[PDB]
Amino acid sequence: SVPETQVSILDNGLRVASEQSSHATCTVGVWIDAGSRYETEKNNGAGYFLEHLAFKGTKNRPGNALEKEVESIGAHLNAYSTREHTAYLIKALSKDLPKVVELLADIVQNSSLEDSQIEKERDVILREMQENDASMQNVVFDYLHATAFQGTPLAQAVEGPSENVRRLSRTDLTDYLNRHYKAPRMVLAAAGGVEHQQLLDLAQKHLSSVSRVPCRFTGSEIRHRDDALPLAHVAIAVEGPGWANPDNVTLQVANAIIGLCQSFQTFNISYSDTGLLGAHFVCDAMSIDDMVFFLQGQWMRLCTSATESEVTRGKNILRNALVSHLDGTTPVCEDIGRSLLTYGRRIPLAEWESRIQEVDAQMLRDICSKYFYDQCPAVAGYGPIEQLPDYNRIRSGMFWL
Amino acid sequence: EFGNLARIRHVISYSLSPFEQRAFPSYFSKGIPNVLRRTRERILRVAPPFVVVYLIYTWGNQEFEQSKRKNPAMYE
Image 1: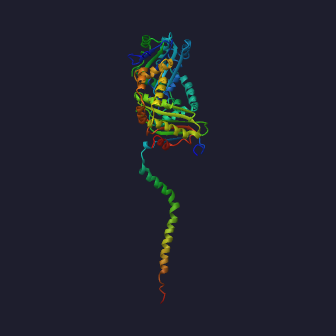
Image 2: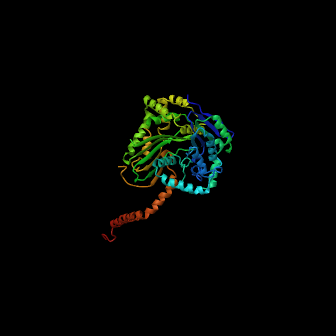
């Protein structure tokens, strides 16, 4: 009974997708298939710095008058960038649907990058990075990406190295903007109280101008020993299958089974036919090795012996979590934008439920043995990590005798 | 034990998986140069004592023989 996500396509290739619902406020966003994976180490912070510059004024709406408009209807304006996708989204009321779309049009095209602003946003970005190091789990996941995807564009961070940040100019940005903002790589996603025909007419009216035009898992480890920190963060991952491979669903159930360290989180990060599947835990130094041992046993267990009931637990757990319908509009659309960018279609919740209920214990331990057993992991540690075991002990813990 | 051995800071340490690296990379490529590099730095400290051991050993042997040699003037 969940309403279907209807997708149309303009000549530009900008797929305009929408999923109407009763809620009177909507989350209209633009997703773009452009991240740090498409950068070539000479423009490693171009997407991040453009994400900073995108709300500082356009040609038609110069400066803060633009954001005055998004204050005037009381709407909320957000943007984010990952290694593969960039999103500019607005939460607003339903009746303010046209102007919001027009605002989004300016943000993707006709944007203006002021040289004055460029220096101010450089100091913002530089400073944030200079303090970003504070967030350990971000440092550990960046280290894990770097040591797992050495020599590839997937190792480099979204923010880029301070070097590039300082060394960036309007023209470079202009390039990234004019290169990675093509209309066939763009989805206009709407969730909530929107009509699809009105949204399609608004996309035809504005946004109809947008121009129309592998990775290797290096199993290895990076350890940043700094003994003055109170807690240690350790992430261990193996290679993931990718977006389009259905056993992801089964792997998600495996994560739902795992769900000794103060904090233990499992992740299945997916990129275009690659990814990182693993666990991140933050612990006191004198516990670290025991955690690792614990964690490896669980994984090995699933690969070795997994019952029927726990599987059911994961199935159900995932089900409720996977549930996103009417979770929130922002989430809803976020899902429409990512589904049109990655799968090329919006997978409905009934298909997700079918793929969940076809998962049993035998295929779960088969897929877990395919992806976890006797695999070389990527290890990233930060903090008092002397008792964190080196690569032979972790690699030997990746199988059982 | 591990964890309480020492205090270091800001020393990042990268590494690779064994199966992801060749077994004897550039083994004889640089091994020979290095072994030779090594031998140079230690040969002058090591070798001349054993050289003079060889000279003393030979000397002793020959001297001993001569010692055993019969005096021409002996019993004549």
